[PDB]
Image: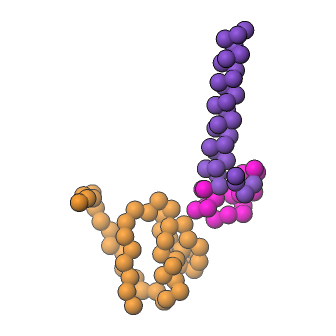
Chain colours: A purple, B orange
Amino acid sequence: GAISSVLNDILSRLDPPEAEVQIDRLITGRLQSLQTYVTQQLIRAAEI
Amino acid sequence: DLCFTNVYADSFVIRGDEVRQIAPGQTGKIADYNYKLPDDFTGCVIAWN
């Protein structure tokens, strides 16, 4: 949902108040990606 | 209904179009070189003509 998936580009494009919102969007997305990966790895490791 | 450790009252005078610059994370002559409010500023801004 952010304006870009590149983080330096958001930082160099937007002012800090709005860059904070965009970076929070990226942080939520990437943190969810890690949580999904770790949960899936835990289940697969139980199978192994 | 609130208590505070301390209150700082900052007073100055600026023209009309720079009052919008008294806000967190602003850009402009005031918010850049005169009086910058922090991004997480907690408090009240009072002005009058």
Asked if residue B17 lies left or right of residue A42, the reply is left
* Image-quadrant location for residue A15: bottom right
Q: Can residue B46 be spotted in the picture?
A: yes
Return the residue nearer the eye: B16 or A48: A48
Residue plotted at (67% across, 17% down):
A43
Residue A44, relative to residue A23: is it above or below?
above
Residue B31 shown left or right of residue A33 in the figure: left
- Which is the main secondary structure of the residues drawn in magenta? helix
Q: Where is residue A26 in the image (x, y as percent from the top left)?
A: 67, 47
**Percent coordinates x, y for residue A6 in the rendering:** 76, 51
Image side of residue B20 versus residue B11, left or right: right
Q: Nearer the viewer, residue B47 or B7?
A: B47
Task: Decide: is A21 above or below B19.
Answer: above
Residue A8 in sight in this render: no
The quadrant the C terminus of chain A occupies is top right
Q: Is residue A23 left or right of residue B6?
A: right
Name the residue rendered at 42%, 86% in the picture. B13
Instruction: Give percent across and percent down for residue B1.
Output: 23, 60
* Stretch of the chain drawn in magenta: A5-21
Query: Does residue A14 belong to the magenta stretch?
Result: yes
- Say whether residue B46 is magenta: no
In percent of width and height, residue B21 lies at 52, 77
What residue appears at the point 66 percent right and 43 percent down from the top-left corner? A29
> Relative to B43, does residue B13 appear above or below in the rendering?
below
